[PDB]
Amino acid sequence: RAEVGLVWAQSTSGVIGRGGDIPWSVPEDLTRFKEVTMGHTVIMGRRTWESLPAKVRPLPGRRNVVVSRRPDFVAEGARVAGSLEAALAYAGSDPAPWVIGGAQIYLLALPHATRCEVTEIEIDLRRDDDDALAPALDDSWVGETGEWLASRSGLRYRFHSYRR
Ligand SMILES: NC(=O)C1=CN([C@@H]2O[C@H](COP(=O)(O)OP(=O)(O)OC[C@H]3O[C@@H](n4cnc5c(N)ncnc54)[C@H](OP(=O)(O)O)[C@@H]3O)[C@@H](O)[C@H]2O)C=CC1
Ligand SMILES: CCOc1ccc(OCC)c(NCc2cnc3nc(N)nc(N)c3c2C)c1
Image 1 (cartoon, rainbow, N blue to C red):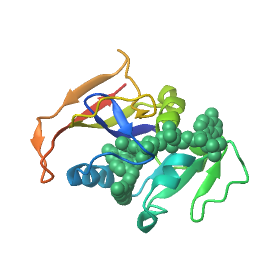
Image 2 (cartoon, rainbow, N blue to C red; image 1 turned 90 degrees about the horizontal axis):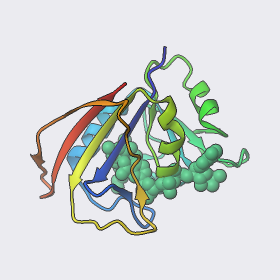
Image 3 (cartoon, helix red, strand yellow; image 1 turned 90 degrees about the vertical axis):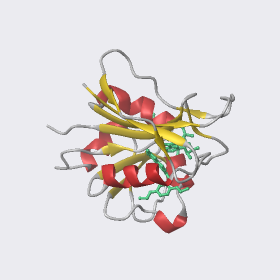
């Protein structure tokens, strides 16, 4: 009944995070992310929660769920869950909960997911051993890809939407 989605931005090289942060600024991607997730449950790993800017934590108008192995973790204004299955239970009757990162939580959620919304960013980031990486999609997914677009930031980006 519920369609579980994943939403992320990556470099063409597959990087989603570096130094505990996102290593670009593409406002158009932030706009997309906001539009995808407004009004829905958003599920995220503990590190992603801690990486959010304090002026958007918890994310407004969304039910925030934070996944940790530590049931005692305190996340003000969010629900803490000990597994993806527990996180999805907190979504309740939300028809389209979203998993919003990071690398570890995407891999946990991927086998439950039926939708992925991906932003690809043309930025010269050579992937390093400590980088947080995007999940790889297999042949079960079918996608449509939008045109490359020029950002007001100067970078080129494009949107992909995958379903199965
Ligand atoms: N470009 C993008 O679209 C986005 C990028 N980011 C970036 O990604 C990075 C964060 O990713 P990552 O470091 O992988 O961290 P995650 O956000 O995936 O958080 C990982 C944490 O999740 C919990 N966890 C992992 N596996 C399990 C499990 N099996 N059961 C219960 N809890 C589990 C643990 O919390 P605990 O240690 O408390 O037990 C672990 O430390 C940052 O750089 C961030 O900026 C984040 C979101 C989107
Ligand atoms: C509702 C506002 O959300 C955010 C605002 C600003 C932010 O950082 C500023 C440096 C945010 N950071 C996390 C974040 C940023 N961009 C993203 N882009 C995409 N496409 N998907 C995400 N999951 C995703 C996430 C989780 C999220």
